[PDB]
Structures are given as structure tokens and as C-alpha cells.
Length: 113
Length: 171
Ligand SMILES: CCCCCCCCCCCCCCCCCC(=O)OC[C@H](COP(=O)(O)OCCN)OC(=O)CCCCCCCCCCCCCCCCC
Ligand SMILES: CCCCCCCCCCCCCCCCCC(=O)OC[C@H](COP(=O)(O)OCCN)OC(=O)CCCCCCCCCCCCCCCCC
Ligand SMILES: N=C(N)NC(=N)NCCc1ccc(I)c(Cl)c1
Image (cartoon, rainbow over all chains, first blue to last red; front, top):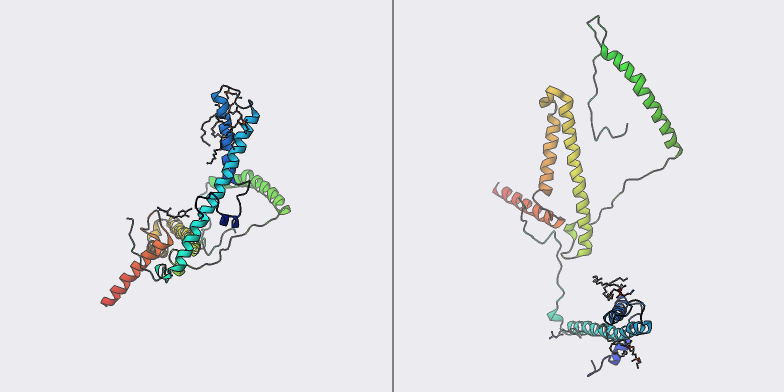
């Protein structure tokens, strides 16, 4: 909500992404793939070379990805909060219907002959 | 024996007694005795042995009972949770009805073979029962298509019921 803010303060009333979040694991896997591609384009032993460099690729991807997921989760909470508050404010636009059973509702039968 | 005689009836057996009008020996009579001694006897003992093993390990299995849930008639439209149970029930009853028609067809085929050249008159009851059950099955399930469902079955029934009302209205 707050102008030009990545994580408005109201977002702290939401639970943070777990560090075992499957999306965070995928992001970390992307960091690992980036490390391997880095070795490959420089003709270094792909798996073994420069493990410190590979570690930083994983850690930096996870670090940024954690805050993106935190903001992603927040923005969908805001979408739900806005939509339900609007439904409360305009009941006549969202009437609760009378539900009829299939014994009462007429549906045409189309034979497959 | 093993199956219910009521579900799978078989008229009483009437075998005539031998009345040989020839002095010759009957080859079938001595072949039957040889079959009993050389085939039935050793086979029977092997089975009696196996039955002695099955009696030492007796354990049971059960026939699943399905409690009745509300039909699709009682389901509010687009209420998947109640629709799902009614739909699953309808599919279970559909398979059972298929097997019912198979039982009636198996009675009919057994009668035709059993009665020989007199089947056209001696199997009139089985023909009638087969005709009635096939008519009922056709009304319930025919022409629904590959994507059949309880919803489509209900629509077929309602269409049939509407025509029956109109035909009576003519009377
Ligand atoms: C649990 C993991 C399951 C794997 C999931 C894979 C998902 C796709 C990830 C794409 C990124 C792959 C890593 C970047 C490529 C680095 C590997 C390479 O370029 O060369 C192979 C290299 C061996 O050759 P070398 O250069 O001599 O290095 C010696 C190191 N021992 O390195 C090696 O020794 C082997 C390294 C892995 C080889 C990767 C081959 C590329 C596969 C691309 C196909 C697309 C992926 C499949 C599509 C479905 C995605 C789930
Ligand atoms: C959207 C969901 C998915 C999330 C996407 C997130 C994308 C953004 C996340 C950041 C992506 C970049 C991560 C780069 C990791 C590799 C960095 C590395 O290994 O550098 C090793 C070394 C330099 O390390 P050094 O700068 O000295 O560390 C001290 C920093 N004060 O020197 C080297 O040999 C490295 C050479 C390879 C680097 C390629 C060129 C880029 C230069 C990077 C400089 C250092 C980057 C530090 C990353 C920190 C980011 C938090
Ligand atoms: N369609 C537009 N031009 N506006 C628009 N994005 N409407 C949709 C509303 C929306 C969607 C996602 C989030 I997260 C939030 Cl907070 C609000």
C-alpha cells in the first residue's frame, strides 16, 4: 500500500515464507544452475571448480528470492483483502442466490445415438 | 454347493434309468468305471489333501457394504461435495445393474441349452424376464453417451416422465 515501498509495514502481520518453501528451493536450484553455467562458459571443471563461487550463487539467489516470495505472498493477501472488503461494501451487487436441487431444475437431455 | 440356487435356478434333474435291450456290452459303462478309478479317484485324493491344508489356515474375507448417500436429485446445483457422493453412488449402481442384466442373460442362455429342441416353449419365462429387465436397463442407461453421469441420467428420466404425463393428459 505504502508509496514506493517494497514491503509495507502492514505485511508483517503475515507469516513469512518458510525457509523450506518449495519455491525457495527451486530458486536455490536456479542459483546452482547459474554456478554450473558460470564454470562451463569459462571452461572450468563444471562440478568441482570454485565451490566458494558456487556457494555465493546459491546463497544470493535464495536471499533475493526470499524477499520476492515475501512480497509475492503479500500482494496476493492485499488482493484478497480488497476483494472481500468490496463485497461487504456492496451487498446488492453480490446477492446470495437461492440454490435449487437437480430434482427441481430442468435440464434438457441430448441423446447420443 | 457354492452358488445360490435361487439366483441361478436349475430345474430338477430327471435321468432315465438304464434299460438295455441288447446282449452286447456297453463300452461307455466300462469306460466310466475306468475313468472313476484312474482319474476321479487320484484327483479326489489330491484335493482332499489340499483341503486338509486349507482347514489348518482358515481366514475370512468380506463383501463390501456401501451405505446409501443422497442422490443427485437432492444435490444443490454446482455443489461438488454432494454431487461427488451422489455421482459415485450412481456409478456403483450402474455397474451392479450391468451385472444384473448379465445374470438374467445367463439364465436365458442356460435354459436354451438345457431344454434342447423344446427350448422355444420351455424357456418362455426366461425370455419374458430378460425382456423386462432389458427394457428397464435401456430406460435407465441407454443413449447417455461416453460421458454419462447421474445428471444426464436424471435429464433422461425427466424427459421420459414428461412424455408419460402428456400421453396421460391425452387420455
Ligand atoms: C537432481 C538434479 C536433476 C537435474 C535437473 C536438470 C534441470 C536443468 C538444469 C539446466 C542447467 C544444467 C547445468 C548447466 C550445464 C552445466 C553442465 C555442462 O555444461 O557440461 C556438462 C558438465 C560435464 O562436462 P565438463 O565441462 O567437462 O565438466 C566436468 C565436470 N565434472 O557437467 C556435468 O558433469 C554434469 C552436469 C549436469 C549436466 C546438465 C545437462 C544439461 C541438461 C539440459 C536439458 C534440459 C533439462 C531437462 C528439462 C526438464 C527440466 C526439469
Ligand atoms: C526471480 C527469482 C529468482 C531470483 C533471481 C535473483 C537474481 C539476483 C541475485 C544475484 C544474482 C547474482 C549472483 C552472483 C553470484 C556469484 C558472485 C561470485 O561468486 O563472485 C565471486 C568473486 C567475487 O566475489 P566478491 O564480489 O569479492 O564478494 C564480496 C562482495 N563484496 O569473483 C568471481 O569470480 C565471480 C565471477 C562470476 C560473476 C559473474 C559476473 C557478475 C559479477 C558479480 C560480482 C559479485 C556479485 C556479488 C553478489 C551479491 C548479491 C547479493
Ligand atoms: N487489471 C488492472 N489494470 N489492474 C489490476 N491489476 N486489477 C486486478 C487487481 C489486483 C490484482 C493483483 C493484486 I497482488 C492486487 Cl493487490 C490487485
